[PDB]
Image (tube, rainbow over all chains, first blue to last red; front, top):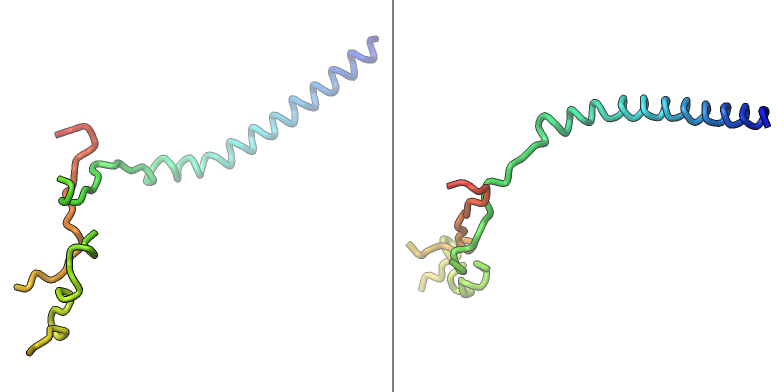
Length: 55
Length: 39
């Protein structure tokens, strides 16, 4: 009974802690790559090329 | 597609010309169509 609730609390605490660590790692990894993607890998396809043959 | 336009004889421009302006071969000329949704 009550011991089982304690086991549930402990397991859930473990899940919360590992998710905390995972989220921190994800943010730390993403932020530099986030900058990389955001600043100067952005492009715009203004045109598309077409042979004069079909026109 | 320009590879089909010019027969084998047209490639002989410059020094390769068979000496017993000439519209030297170029790839099929492209028109650039705007696609960004503006004019």
